[PDB]
Length: 70
Length: 70
DNA sequence: CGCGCG
DNA sequence: CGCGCG
Image 1 (cartoon, rainbow over the protein chains, first blue to last red):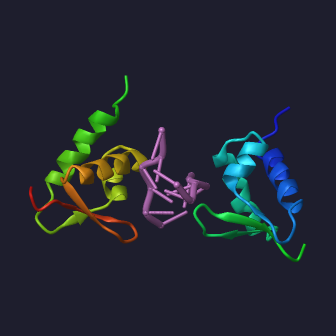
Image 2: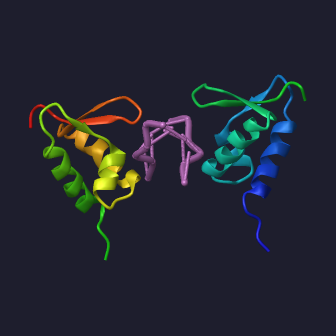
């Protein structure tokens, strides 16, 4: 009856996988689309990087790329 | 019914003002010596630094010395 | 303001 | 793990 963070994780993963290898996005942009708090978006983005689905580039703010192996 | 920001500020300010000239303390130490969450301790420490009561030296964890004015 | 942090 | 961030 409850959808913890897993549904957020799934929404974010689906979004990043839709990116072109050459494109990138940010937490603020993602938060804006999925209408979710940037904090929630970040909690998933960093977890997703641990799974190698996305790659973060320490820009200001960080830019997120889909793993090019995809 | 709860010790608020302003009140924790006073508690932290007193501990820091009781340090000898060149000795420091850390947020976790104050957290332990007192019965307050580390986050709440740091919230006060950085404000105390803005007020020139304490001085922070980066390290892990950050060291907090009494400002020489005191 | 980069912050994800338990 | 540095985090204080409203």
